[PDB]
Length: 20
Image 1 (tube, rainbow, N blue to C red):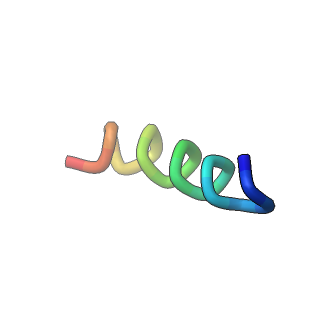
Image 2 (image 1 turned 30 degrees about the vertical axis):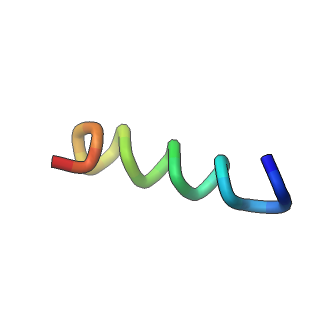
């Protein structure tokens, strides 16, 4: 995870529909 690398990158991706 590295503090917030994976937490912000998964939450933001899925919401923007896998970041279209």
